[PDB]
Image (cartoon, coloured by chain):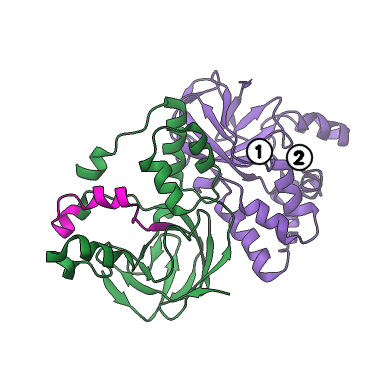
Chain colours: A purple, B green
Amino acid sequence: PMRYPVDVYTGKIQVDGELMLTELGLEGDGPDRALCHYPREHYLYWAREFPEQAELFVAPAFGENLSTDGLTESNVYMGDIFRWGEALIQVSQPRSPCYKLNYHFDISDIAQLMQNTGKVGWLYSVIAPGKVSADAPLELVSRVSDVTVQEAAAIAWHMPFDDDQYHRLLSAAGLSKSWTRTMQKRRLSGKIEDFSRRLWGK
Amino acid sequence: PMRYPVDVYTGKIQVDGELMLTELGLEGDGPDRALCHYPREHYLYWAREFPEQAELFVAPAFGENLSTDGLTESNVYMGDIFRWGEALIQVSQPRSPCYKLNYHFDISDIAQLMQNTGKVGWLYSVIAPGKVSADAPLELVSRVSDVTVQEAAAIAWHMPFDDDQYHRLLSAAGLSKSWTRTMQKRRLSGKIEDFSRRLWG
């Protein structure tokens, strides 16, 4: 039963107190995307990649609510349920990188790079609202799937069209509504949707 | 491909024009329970069970939005995705019987009996909003699970405590938030929640 200590941030500013996790997110901050998570470890990577702006790559530069060390996309699975203090949360999707990040860091291809590396983080849906805190760690209570956030990112963005793999992703407990809609549409249309608008803003 | 004709009803009155299906349900009518489905076959059963009120047991007596013939809880699966006209919908849970039905039929134990038989029908979540109609059938496009609605009802209500079977249910694609919360809580608490308040008041 590993515990992952969490640094919390809301509208973005570090929080030390006890606070309330509602169905719609933490107080002061849709239901499938109420909580953003980014692995603190990835900052080291970005800093190496862009030395002359290493000072920009610290939490919560990527807009995250939860910052941790020891959880990454390859050891966190779709549908995973974690207890956090009094609340329950479930992994709903990988976070899709967005062009707005490029302007936030004033680096032209960050979003593209995030997507390519798969160092994107994940969003939660809140299964039970409750009292939470910075001093209360995450604890995995149910793993109900075999698809790691990493694999979900790969199915989404790295692989050529594979109906079988979309079927697999659609079978993942907790999958967000948008990702269900996106993947189902691929299966029916036979086409992978455009990423350009999301990634560049052009 | 097998496609299922459907009678629609919106709060209940039979609609047969086109109408818009939204994230929050049909136009005129939470996101996990936007669409209620009940199999038309069950009415025959209820009529036999309560002969002196057989006239009450016709669609949409059980409040359903969708009425069909050929789909039942043993051949519909958790997480199933169906195309309906222009929209996409996903099976999210068995419908939980409620005491209000007892007053609707003015028969004292209908909800309890529904739960016990497992003749409960199911709710959908709306994956894509779109134009729908009575003249547009349901078509199964993705089956992503091995838990039938029947099995989910049994895990819920018919079985003694079985952590393994709750794990199984928590692994079902599309499972509603409330059922996820309910089943997770069983696993942590070691206790099956009370049904009485829901079944009676």
The subunit letter for the residue under badge 2 reads A
Relative to A185, say whether A40 is above or below.
Answer: above
Instruction: Please tell me which residue is depicted at 41% across the width and 32% down the height of the picture.
Output: B161
Q: Specify the quadrant that holds the C terminus of chain A.
A: bottom right
Residues marked 1 and 2, same chain: yes
Across and down, in percent, residue B186 comes to: 42, 31
The residue that label 2 is drawn on is A119
Relative to B88, say whether B185 is above or below.
Answer: above
Counting labels gives: 2
Q: Specify the quadrant that holds the N terminus of chain A.
A: top right
Answer whether residue B107 is magenta in the image: yes
The secondary structure type at the circle numbered 1 is loop
What kind of residue is marked 1? Tyr
Instruction: Judge the density around disc 2: few (<14), some (14-19), many (≥20) Cα neighbours within 10 Å.
Output: many
Of A183 and A40, nearer the camera is: A183
What kind of residue is marked 2? Lys
Answer whether residue A144 is magenta in the image: no
Relative to B143, say whether A111 is above or below.
Answer: above
Residue A202 appears anywhere in the view = no
State which tag comes first along the sequence, 1 or 2.
1
Label drawn at residue A77:
1
Relative to B6, say whether A12 is above or below.
Answer: above
Across and down, in percent, residue A106 comes to: 78, 44
Residue range in magenta is B102-123
Residue A114 occupies which quadrant of the picture?
A: top right
Image-based side of A128 in relation to A113, left or right: left
The subunit letter for the residue under badge 1 reads A
Instruction: Judge the density around disc 1: few (<14), some (14-19), many (≥20) Cα neighbours within 10 Å.
Output: many
Q: Which residue lies furthest to the top in this view?
A: A135
Instruction: Please tell me which residue is depicted at 58% across the width and 48% down the height of the picture.
Output: A175
